[PDB]
Length: 89
Length: 89
Image 1 (cartoon, helix red, strand yellow):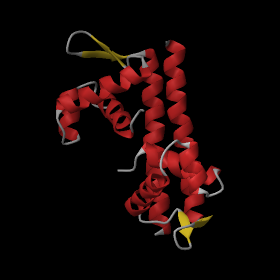
Image 2 (cartoon, rainbow over the protein chains, first blue to last red; image 1 turned 180 degrees about the vertical axis):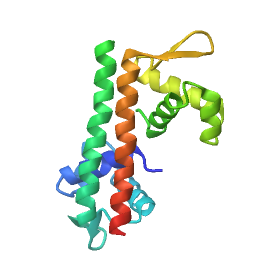
Image 3 (cartoon, helix red, strand yellow; image 1 turned 90 degrees about the horizontal axis):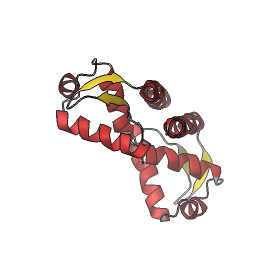
Image 4 (cartoon, rainbow over the protein chains, first blue to last red; image 1 turned 180 degrees about the horizontal axis):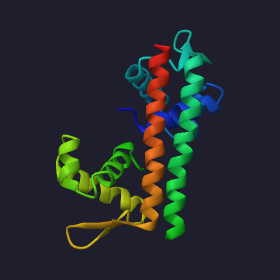
């Protein structure tokens, strides 16, 4: 089963121009940590979200553009649950 | 942080007419496991998804109707990701 954390990671990596180092510092976590969770996700899905050239991301794949876009929808809907909660709070 | 599992649980509990026992057997898990994950979710959200009367769920709350609906959209969108993966495999 895919996890929300891996969805947040590919969204953030995509919004830091594929710079995994810059993303790690954005999320206050280690850079190897983010790379692990993404490859678990890609192994779990069986598709590459990010094309690589060595230990380095080069571009978002066709499949990844669709998957990341939908991850943003999931992350925004998770946020709306917390806003629904707080309005009734 | 909220988890996909807890979103799957409140949705499944809601589609087994609030019967946690039938839901546990559906998901091949324990009934205490589902209850535990639901109360964690509700503590994080600070709202009750299910109105209670003793060790018993009576109805879905105004807020819970919205949260469960949005949890369903999320669970559907998680499925769209794996359908995107399968296509591109």
